[PDB]
Image (tube, coloured by chain):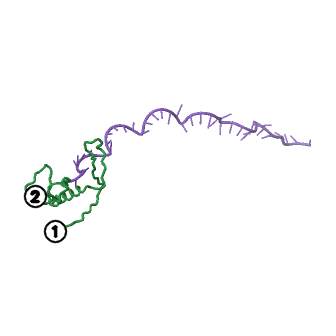
Amino acid sequence: MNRHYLITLTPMDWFFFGGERTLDDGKSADYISHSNKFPQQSALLGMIRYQLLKQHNLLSQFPYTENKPTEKEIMKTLIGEQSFRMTERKAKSLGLG
RNA sequence: AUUAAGACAUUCGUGAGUGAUUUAUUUCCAUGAAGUGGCGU
């Protein structure tokens, strides 16, 4: 059985959502960045995954530390393998734990 | 872990240079140093 939550986001300051043109791309005019009005749903997914491991205290802190083969499947059962990969759009399941 | 992260609109810069408070203007106009004699027909 599943548990459902309503998550409300209140901005504490000015925000910005990146578009196709970002301040440090290799293209020509890489000094003007414009903000999309909404975040991508992948950003929402990354938000939830980050907070989920924050509550469970499982992060990468500094060097590129590797994780022992218990944090590995705890992150499997927590968030899964990948980010929102649009390649697997025809998959009849969320690829996230 | 999310088209992310990182970045003082900052460095240099005298409100400064040129410029008489000067020009024009009579301390002047009016005006008597003057008036009277007095005493014994």
Q: Nearer the viewer, residue A76 or A66?
A: A76
Q: Residue furthest bottom?
A: A1
- How many other residues sit within 10 Å of disc 2, few (<14), some (14-19) or many (≥20)? few
Position of A18 compared to B35: left or right?
A: left
Say above or below: B20 vs A6.
above
Q: Chain of mark 1?
A: A
- Percent from the top left, x then y, of residue A4? 21, 66
Q: Which mark is residue A1?
A: 1
The disc label shown at residue A73, or none: 2
Q: Residues within 10 Å of mark 1 (few under 14, many from 20)?
A: few
Mark 2 belongs to which amino acid? Glu
Answer whether labels 1 and 2 touch (C-beta < 8 Å).
no
Q: Residue at 28% across / 53% down in the picture?
A: A17
Q: Position of residue A95 (x, y in %)?
A: 16, 58
Q: CA distance from mark 1 to mark 2?
A: 22 Å
Label 1 vs 2, first from the N-terminus: 1
Tell me, by letter, which chain the rendering colours green: A
Which quadrant would residue A84 be assigned to in this image?
Answer: bottom left
Q: Which residue is at the front of the view, A74 or A11?
A: A74
- Per the rendering, the colour in which chain B appears is purple
